[PDB]
Amino acid sequence: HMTEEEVRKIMEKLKKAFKQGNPEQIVSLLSPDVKVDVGNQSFSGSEEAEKMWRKLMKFVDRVEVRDVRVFENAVMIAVEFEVNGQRYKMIFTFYVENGKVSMVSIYISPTMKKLMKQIL
Amino acid sequence: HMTEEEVRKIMEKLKKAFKQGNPEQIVSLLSPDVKVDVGNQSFSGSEEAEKMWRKLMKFVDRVEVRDVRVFENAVMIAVEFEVNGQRYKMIFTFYVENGKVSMVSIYISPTMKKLMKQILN
Ligand SMILES: [Cl-]
Ligand SMILES: [Cl-]
């Protein structure tokens, strides 16, 4: 259980990590047993989460935080990604437990899934 | 891509099915290829989703909606379930595509983890 102010803190740090593009910042906010579900792929590790993040960031030329909201212990972040001149929209949901993200839920538009399945 | 007004209609239908009892409304909102992620388990297809949903709702003796919120194509519902005298907080995130729910993400309390394991297994 975390206070409203507690969740807002991680939110601002998650927001700063996305915009500035520092991957180490993102990873430090994840719990060691963080569960990441995105599309058909699922990841159990925190170190595995970092691997998939960097594997995505190596194709992304431009990151842009569109909007950020906080619902209970969830932090939602709308992100636009530019890959090969093309823009894509992703939705991230970070569920926080004890000051760190315990679960990450990412929505992927059908056209994005193609790219993820292509540029894999 | 769906308009803000189109996502709100689904939200109200979702909100209504929670403020009321029947899960028969939520299954009608599900896409045939819907993906439900609860705990470490994932459920694919409306058939498996309607099964998992029904089994869970049969364990719940009381439902209270704490809050509802819309964010892009995502519908968030904060709920309190009561199973065997004990009460648990949960969050439902419904991702909408073309008027139906393509993906459902369910967060549960750590204290509900063992209990959720018994129901689904
Ligand atoms: Cl997109
Ligand atoms: Cl907008």
Image (cartoon, coloured by chain):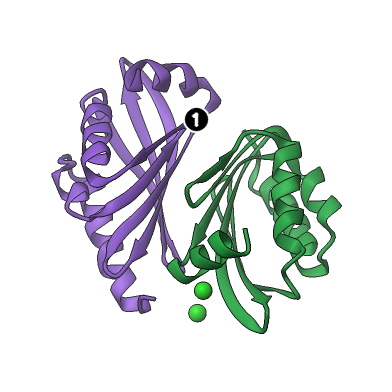
Chain colours: A green, B purple
Q: How many marks?
A: 1
- Relative to A109, is A9 on the left or the right? right
Using the rendered image of the protein, determine whether residue B34 is visible from the camera's viewpoint: yes
A36 with respect to B70 (left or right): right
Quadrant of res A58: bottom right
Q: Nearer the viewer, residue B91 or B119?
A: B119
Front-most of residues A9 and B58: B58
Examine the image and state in which quarter residue B80 appears: top left
Q: Residue furthest bottom?
A: A85
Question: Is A4 in front, or is B77?
Answer: B77
In percent of width and height, residue A28 lies at: 82, 44
Circle 1 marks a residue in which chain?
B
Question: Which residue is depicted at the point 46% across and 67% down?
Answer: A109
Q: Amino acid at mark 1?
A: Asn
Locate the C terminus of chain B by quadrant.
Answer: top left
Q: Which residue is mark 1?
A: B40
Q: Does A63 sit above or below residue B79?
A: below
Task: Decide: is B14 above or below B65.
Answer: below
Residue A70, picture quadrant? bottom right
Circle 1: element type: loop
Where is A71 relative to B56, above or below? below
Q: Residues within 10 Å of mark 1 (few under 14, many from 20)?
A: few
